[PDB]
Image 1 (tube, helix red, strand yellow):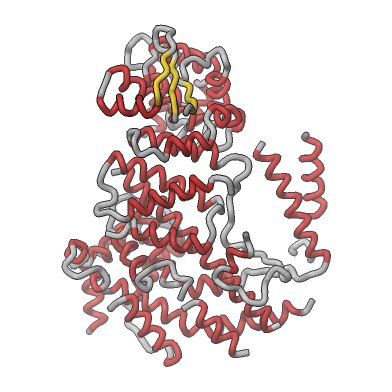
Image 2 (tube, each protein chain N blue to C red):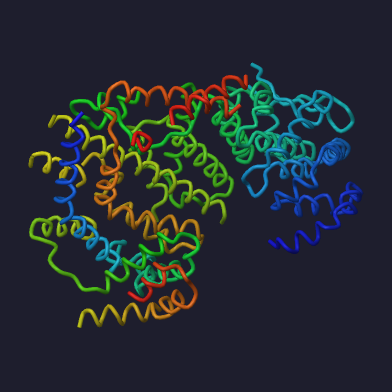
Length: 146
Length: 457
């Protein structure tokens, strides 16, 4: 019947509405990754292990030695890492409150700072290793983007 | 770990095969060589080799030969249908049915063995376990032989080797396996072996089947007026109830401890129970309502050794299946809202759905993120990959839900839609026949081909 038209219209409207908050959720995840130690219990061995950006180094190593394992995972990790070092901006007043609530629940010159932190983690070697090993279009292109 | 070197060594294999059974470390070496090269196993494994191995096991009566024979059934821990069939044929004949220790239930469990001297010794299962715990040559040998025989029997039935399962199940019933496993007095190794045997001989049998959480196609009439949390399970609506109860109790008891993965004896039992739970969940026996609590317990048994890594990977897979079920429930809720509409209120309902009972956690989701972060720092590559995937998925559920809703293809159409039910009915018999006359299969294939712009639909 014609109910397919109404269903598709409702789906399109819902997707358009949810678009403002998808980026907010992605930013919330990026922020959570930015300061991983903020989540784990303070004073625990994980706090010290993750104190010096341990999660960052582990993710960098996995991405470097993970291109063959799963291209999608490597691409997503690279995109998230680039978004983290790519500043931030208001995701819309409608989704601003949602992002704030999500950050609160999941967690009880700045560009230069994060760039230097990523460099210390060893993102330079990551990008150069991705570049000078792979012909896959997305892999090399996203390494250039990073 | 050398394909080229393995092939070069295998080039001259007849000499090694002939010099087997002379007390030299060659039979084990030969088995190790033919452990990964499925092609090598096919080329060098035949009836003669299996018969020679069986004769050597009978003569020596030592567990090592049985373990070596069992290890040949599984190649790369995936399958070996030709080798598995040959091993089952060689080790299932009544004539060879003398090197396997029989088990029976008496008013308890009793194991009967033929002894190396062609004797007939029957010992109580509980009494045998007590003697083995005390420590004795005969008791230790009996326990080791029983463990190796159970492992070999379970391996022989790997995947769907019905030709051997049909006999193994009758030899050791599901009820007997459940009674033996739920003892807590026998050594942990024997309990783990029994659990593995039960999982691989009475869980993955013909009745059970795999389940796909995210059913991309849904029936228009199926969608109800309103889908409650229980609705997603009530609408869906077996016999191993005691097995499920034992699994749940063991998992809960493991969770209610400090350093849950500490004792190797209990570590093996946990690694077997987790595998059984994963198989049951993937089989669809459990429901969403109980699935939430099971996932909460599993996560609690991971927060804050190859066996430990494997158990963590299995728990991660179970959690991923639970997340897929949750995404399916969200899609069902959206479809139910759309059907109720028959605007903006639907927008509010959608925004409130993906924001709550439908949450796999106990601290507002913080537990899942903490567990994923801790696992990410781990060593095992599969564990790291799974943790990274789960972390990147959890915080991006809205996009995945929207994409799923964009792939749902309702079948509200007329009898043409009923063609979908007809196709499902045909595929049921097709899969049943594939698991295990040819006229029915040919007719089903012809009908499917005939059924297959309408081509896109």
